[PDB]
Image (cartoon, rainbow over all chains, first blue to last red; front, side, top):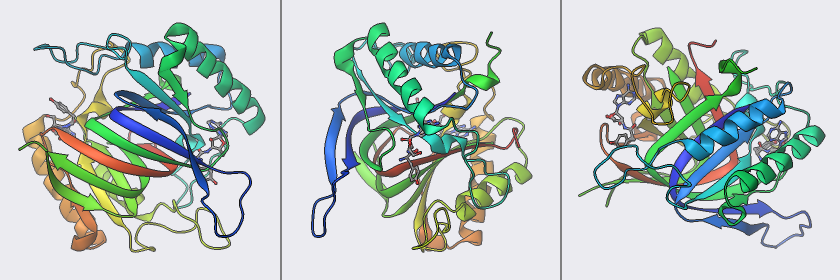
Length: 163
Length: 151
Ligand SMILES: Nc1ncnc2c1ncn2[C@@H]1O[C@H](CO)[C@@H](NC(=O)[C@H](N)Cc2ccc(O)cc2)[C@H]1O
Ligand SMILES: Nc1ncnc2c1ncn2[C@@H]1O[C@H](CO)[C@@H](NC(=O)[C@H](N)Cc2ccc(O)cc2)[C@H]1O
């Protein structure tokens, strides 16, 4: 499993509508957060629940905010901050083959959706259901973000010696 | 070397005493981390990928057009947090990151090469070693990660 985590002052997420006509507004705002983390999440074809549990534990525990004087002191839960979780199969874009990315390592969409929904539910259980916001799996999205730092963290659970 | 590439409709980068120093419209924001053991060849690979990866569509083909094809812009942001050591702690420790003073000179070379491979006008950068606020419109979103030590 792969994730890019970014520290933000805020984020507004909109999604492309299913029902689109000519001469119409096509994107609709579905999620908004203030301070916290945006997590772009990619599910690998061979991911297990243990991969997901590692990512969730890490995201919730990363100490990415300063306190009064102390550097890298507080995690997202400590400050009652929010998380915006966005499904992102492009993290499996293989860029070694030339200029056209291929995404064959990404978990197949039907199982990935179920997996994604389990992950969101687990984020809500481990933290606070009011603090977890999501996009719309499988849809084009627009995200207006204020990056704070910036602070960008990348985790691939396959780089980890997980059992 | 590590990069996070995000496809954007625009980005506005500001720094403290906030003041806007860089802005782009459509293109890429590239968060770039330099490893203590990186070589010029690592840099060249990342620059090549940022400039040539086909992260936009043609009318009839997906993933067919790159940033240079569309005459779009790039915002390059130095980001040592990509070497956070999250494997070993929950507080980021940047020991795998290249020493900042030496990294700055290396980064200068990288930016020059971006400008050489593309053009001066289309490359914008942040403020190395400073706090930055970056207002971004992520388009897709489309996020690409490359670690040259993994190829
Ligand atoms: N394996 C997966 N992991 C995470 N998300 C996934 C996975 N498989 C499918 N998805 C979701 O379905 C969408 C299309 O594949 C994925 N969408 C995206 O990655 C962004 N909308 C970017 C995008 C843009 C255009 C495009 O043709 C494909 C993808 C994700 O929401
Ligand atoms: N090895 C490096 N690779 C990329 N950038 C680097 C590297 N070493 C130093 N830098 C630059 O100096 C800053 C940390 O001293 C880096 N900045 C950042 O990572 C972001 N402004 C986040 C940040 C913000 C504040 C802070 O106290 C520490 C980090 C980068 O501009």
